[PDB]
Amino acid sequence: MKTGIVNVSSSLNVRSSASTSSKVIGSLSGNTKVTIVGEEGAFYKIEYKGSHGYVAKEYI
């Protein structure tokens, strides 16, 4: 139930998987609400903008 808050930094690149080679695919907004839904590697799974992208958990 409890959601996580994205670290209101200044910039954050969203990948397509727990791989850097995946490259960028979209940009997420800080302070955005995301209902976590699983995790893999040094990244977590989320669902926003009707789409899904991986994000670092260490930064959050």
Image (cartoon, grey):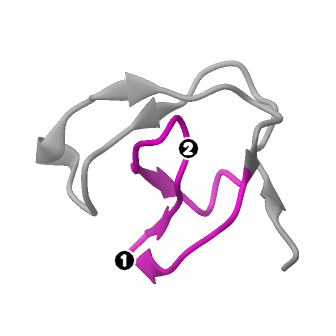
Instruction: Name the spot of residue 39 as percent of width and height, x first.
Output: 46, 78
Q: Secondary structure at mark 2?
A: loop
- Left or right position of 26 against 28: left
Q: Residue furthest front?
A: 50
Decide whether residue 51 is among the magenta residues: yes
- Amino acid found under the numbered disc labelled 1: Gly
**Residue at position x 69%, y 64% from top?**
35
Q: Which image quarter holds the N terminus?
A: bottom right
Neighbour tally class for label 1: few under 14, some 14-19, many 20 plus, Cα within 10 Å: few
Q: Residue furthest left?
A: 21
Instruction: Name the spot of residue 54 as percent of width and height, x first.
Output: 41, 54
Q: Which image quarter holds the C terminus?
A: bottom right
- Left or right position of 58 against 50: right
* Circle 2 residue: 48
* Circle 1 residue: 41
Residue in front for this viewpoint, 13 or 51: 51
Residue in front for this viewpoint, 9 or 44: 44
- Amino acid found under the numbered disc labelled 2: Tyr
Q: Of discs 2 and 1, which sits in the foreground?
A: 2
Mark toward the start of the polypeptide (2 vs 1)? 1
**Residue at position x 11%, y 44% from top?**
21
Neighbour tally class for label 2: few under 14, some 14-19, many 20 plus, Cα within 10 Å: few
> What residue span does the magenta drawing correspond to?
34-60
Residue 23, quarter of the rendered image? top left
